[PDB]
Length: 281
Length: 280
Ligand SMILES: Cc1cnc(Nc2cnn(C)c2)nc1-c1cnn([C@H](CC#N)C2CCCC2)c1
Ligand SMILES: Cc1cnc(Nc2cnn(C)c2)nc1-c1cnn([C@H](CC#N)C2CCCC2)c1
Image (tube, rainbow over all chains, first blue to last red; front, top):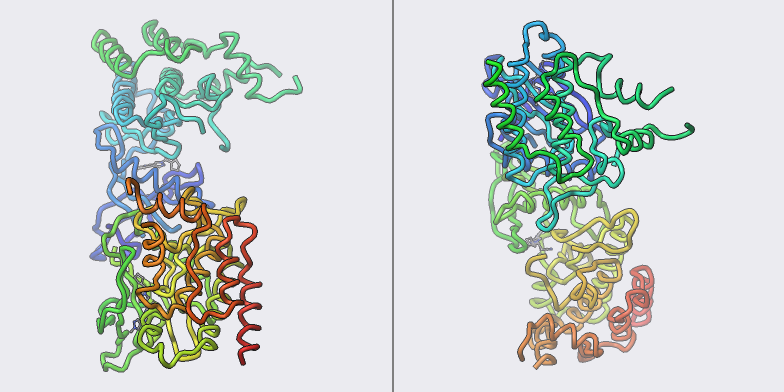
């Protein structure tokens, strides 16, 4: 599909999860005028990592949706995934930099697009396992997409969960992810609640999930994951962001229910968010 | 390393396993004087088949041994594996055509070189899974090599077997390959016994493994099912006419139901070399 000799490195866009994304120009005519693209590649490659990356590529190839980064092709352990280039970058850095120009209505537009991306994911029985503002990308002021599927897994044909590791974003994890490594649509719903908290805290570092959970845990001879599991069991939850509307915080608190089956659906979350936004406007 | 524009098709050498090998000349100076080579390519290309072929290429790249066809390079999915050209072709067809000029001593020379190729494979924790006279190639009257690695697999770091499956040469398969799809050095040893039977039957069609097993099978059920029952009951290929006792004894030990009672390729190498030395 894409040749390596025509792939012109421009700058580093993201790194992590044994992977990196690079802004490249595909210039097969050598004029400096080709199309800018995103190139994901493996770091510390292993046959195991390469197998996961091949599955990642196939997962994104099956996805066509306005709120999911667009698969373009592949370039032939030097395997590279080629995607569209979203110019405004991660929502996390975009919100942190443009917060003064972003009101609650815009946050709901972002939240609505994430839900619709997750609902679509639902229809293919895919679990993201990494839903966070750092894995969401800004295309334009009116459009966000989910931009990485490095931990995404296909549910088995006979189960509603996948059991899975390495370093993990424990402050976004559902109780049953922490204790039994069980990942489900309902675990993505719990993480979407943390994404809503991130958006309404405007990525303020003092208020970040790791900051708030660490203050609640205290400053023992035990692991942070151990303390966090106890805090979640005792109904320890992230606080209401300053000025967060009650209907939005109510949505967060329902996403963070200990019972998997009492968590809302992404379809219900879509509808609720769209209507709250309609009310505000 | 190799460009397609300089790859000149000459003749078809082999086809099978969703793959084909072609005799090509690499003529970059366009004089018809370049080096003749073997080019393997995929047929019914599937990303999965492409992934298997990429691993096959890497497997052959890691192999350098007198009794293993030489990796030369790759040509870019139209991804093509380039190997040396062995001019006398597959041992199966060579033996079938030259049997009147080939005595038991020569069969032992062929058998010895296969064992040494398989032992080398052993050292890399590779299992061939397709050991047969059709995957052996003749370079000269004194040298043979294993020529295809289309089904070859790297053992996991923590296990002595690999569990795998399309159309398969069931009449070369070990009981535990048929029943549980388990492949091992010991499964390659079982197949080596069938290769020894092929060589000593001089590839006579009336005596082929599929011929003999089919006569023994005689239904209601699948051939694979009958074959599993025949092997469980100690149904085995017969002694080739004229096959020395030591050679047949080597076959019967290779075809032990118990994986761990099968000889090693190092033991088989030594035994074959000495029997050839005794025959002079
Ligand atoms: C896929 C993609 C497409 N366009 C852009 N555009 C961009 C980025 N920065 N700017 C200024 C402009 N970025 C990415 C991109 C970078 N990182 N990611 C992953 C996280 C997410 N989503 C990382 C890759 C390594 C692991 C997670 C996606
Ligand atoms: C790799 C190779 C190198 N040189 C030659 N020389 C040759 C062949 N015929 N003659 C007259 C001369 N042949 C091959 C060759 C052809 N087929 N194979 C595989 C089976 C085996 N071993 C096939 C490939 C597709 C499925 C298995 C190797």
